[PDB]
Image (tube, rainbow, N blue to C red; front, side):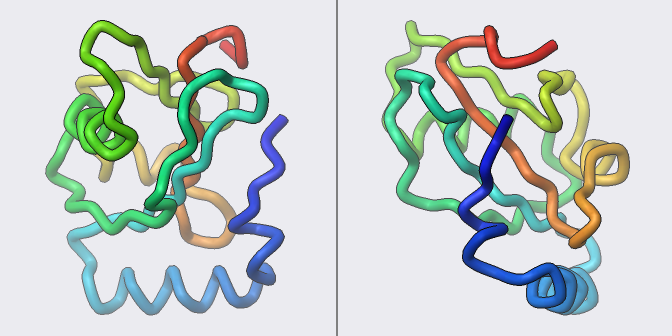
Length: 118
């Protein structure tokens, strides 16, 4: 189970306000929080917060993260949104609706292994 440092760093209200602010200013983009699955071997990521157009796919977003942590192409990465790996043909906008947190953000976990959940 993920202990999100973004959630320990900011209160529920804080997160609710800021996500609503960013969604009002940029309604065609979805706010994303990215943290590494605890105990996974993969390198930690330098950038945690992401504002991405709802027109891009999950496969495209994964490339962004892969490139961010400079993961070799021959190494796997798996995204988790609430213990389940999301469909790569899905758009971040479609994905936002189904998996958005109570606070208005989309939380994405990543790992080098899919032993984490479903």
